[PDB]
Image (tube, grey):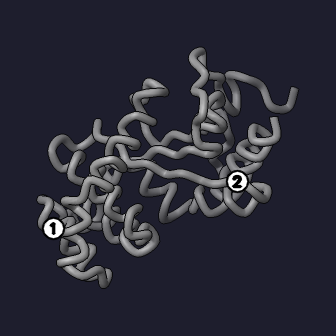
Amino acid sequence: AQYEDGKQYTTLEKPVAGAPQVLEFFSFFCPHCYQFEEVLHISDNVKKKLPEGVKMTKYHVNFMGGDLGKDLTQAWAVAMALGVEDKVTVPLFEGVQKTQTIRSASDIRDVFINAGIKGEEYDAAWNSFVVKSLVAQQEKAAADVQLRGVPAMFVNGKYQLNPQGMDTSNMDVFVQQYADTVKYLSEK
């Protein structure tokens, strides 16, 4: 076939029921994740090729960056609850990996403030049990699929994208192959 299990994707030995249709995992500490966000715009190109009725989910993970890694998972929960993902993703990536100005939860908080979320609104969210449950959801989704590496994308809880098996000489061609694979898997 043109698409082959073990080539553009792998199949989960343990399929996950009731999983999000397109589920992406990342870490703000993850160097390919930075590329995926700022250079490749993977999420946006996948979306442009997906059908109507397809929701896309993106979760942060704990297993990189120790204590700050966990703060970031909680901050991403805050971003999701407030619907401000698109305002904080770039400055969080840059603060962790480019300027290295994010060293504590307070520094994470500063990113949100500078992005225009009010302190009182941020702190209230940070401490809310709605955000506690969003943190639980992120952890459970990653646990369900035995997740030990990022970036990762899972389609319908049974297929896992395999970017290692795609050409990387041309960045644009890589992104479309990736997005076209997600579409293929989606229609499967």
Q: Is residue 151 left or right of residue 46?
A: left
Spot occupied by residue 174 in the image (x, y as percentages of width and height): 67, 50
Q: Is residue 24 above or below residue 171?
A: above
In the image shown, does 125 or 157 lie closer to the viewer?
125
Q: Give the class, few, some or many, for how many residues have Cα within 10 Å of label 2's Cα (few <14, many ≥20).
A: few
Give the secondary structure at mark 1.
helix
Spot occupied by residue 155 in the image (x, y as percentages of width and height): 65, 38
As measured in the structure, the alpha-carbon distance from the residue carrying label 2 to the one carrying label 1 is: 34 Å
Q: Residue at x 18, y 69 (%)?
A: 123
Quarter of the rendering containing residue 87: bottom left
Specify the label residue 107 is tagged with: 1
Q: Is residue 131 left or right of residue 23?
A: left
Q: Is residue 54 above or below residue 146?
A: below
Residue lying furthest right: 1
Spot occupied by residue 175 in the image (x, y as percentages of width and height): 66, 54
Q: Which amino acid, mark 1?
A: Asp
Q: Residue at x 45, y 36 (%)?
A: 141
Q: Give the class, few, some or many, for how many residues have Cα within 10 Å of label 1's Cα (few <14, many ≥20).
A: some
For mark 2, what is the residue?
54
Q: Quadrant of the C terminus?
A: top right
Quarter of the rendering containing residue 48: bottom right
Spot occupied by residue 2 in the image (x, y as percentages of width and height): 85, 32
Q: Is residue 185 visible?
A: yes
Q: Residue at x 73, y 47 (%)?
A: 177
In the image shown, does 111 or 128 lie closer to the viewer?
128
Specify the label residue 151 is tagged with: none
In the image shown, does 109 or 98 lie closer to the viewer?
109
Q: Residue at x 49, y 27 (%)?
A: 145
Q: Which amino acid, mark 2?
A: Val
- Disc tally is 2
Give the secondary structure at mark 2.
loop
